Image (tube, rainbow, N blue to C red; front, side):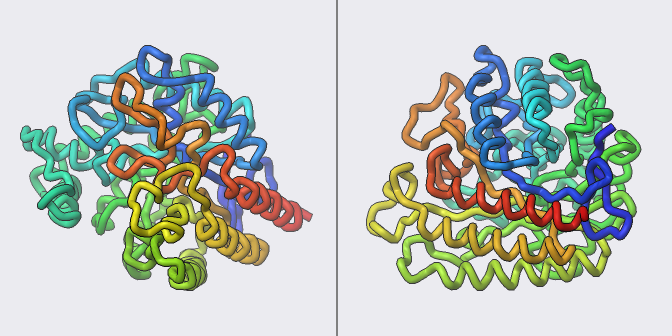
Length: 414
C-alpha cells in the first residue's frame, strides 16, 4: 500500500502521505550477489551490505534488473540474467528476489533499471547483436573508440529495421520482470511497494522522443502503480533533458555526473579538485532549473570520483588500491551533498544515489569462479575506481548527508 508517489505540487516524492527524500546508493550488483552460491552469489555478503547501508541511513538502492548473455563475452556481468532472448538463468533471477526481499526487511525502496546502453550488462549493444546475428560487438578498447561503440548500440532505437525487433525483445524482458513472482516473499514485482520505480535504461544516448514515449507508456501500462523514470544523464542541454523527460508516463527526472570520464577532473592532479567542485555546483543548479521547468522531481542518481591518485601520480595501480585515501572524493561528495540538502529544503531537489557502494568487496581480492570481482565498479572499468568500501572515510560523509536530508524531510512534513 506504501507506493512511492509524486507530490501533487510535482516538486518532490511522497511515501505514506509525507515528503520522501532519496537517501540513496547505487547497488547494481545486488542481483548477482543475492544469487545462490551455485550461480556465483554470496547472499550473506549481500545481507551484510544492505545492513551496512541501513546503518549509513540509506533508504533507496538503484539496482540493475537486467543483464544479457551470452556468458562468454568480456566486460560484463556473469552469469547473466538472460543469456538468450527470453531464456533466463533462474539462479540469477532468484538473486533479484532476495535482493528485493532483503531491501524489504530494511524498509528500503528500489529503482529497477530494466536495461543498459553500455556493455557492462550486455545492454542495447547485445540486443543489436542478437538481431543482426553478429556476435562481434565493437567494444571500446584497443583501436575502437567510444563513439564507434555508441553508434553501434544506438541502432537499438535509431535503426528503423533493427529497432522494432530489438524493442520487441526488450519489451519481452520488461514484461518478464514486472510480472515476476518473488519466490521468497510471494509478491509479484508490479505490486511490490518496495519498488519505487521502473527505469527504462541506464544512460540512453540521444534516444528519440518517440522511443521514450513508447517505452514509458509500455512500462506504466505494465505496472500502473509504479513511478517510471528514464535513466538519463542530463549531460547535454535542456532540450536533450526534455526529449527524455517531457512525457506523461515519465514521472520524475534524473541526472548523472561523471567529472573524470568527461574530461573535467584529473584525479592525478593535486591541484585538480576545484574544477570538479565548480562543475558539480553549476551542474546541480542548472539541472534543478530544468526539472522545475517540467514541474517534475529530480534525483542525482549516479555520480562518482576516484581515490587520491595525486598522492602518487606516476603509479597507475596506486589509484585503485583500497588503502589509498579519498580526500578529494570526500570533499566533492560533501559539497554535492550540502548543496543537495539546501536545494531539497527549497523543494528543488529530491536526493541522490552515490555511484556506488562496494561494501565488503575489494579491488585486491581474487575473481570468483565466474571471473567476477564484485564491488561497485562494473567489469568494463578498473576494479576499485569508484567503489565506496564499508570502512572508507567516505561512509561518515554519506551517513551525515542521509541524516541531513532526513532532517529536511521532517521539516517539509510539518
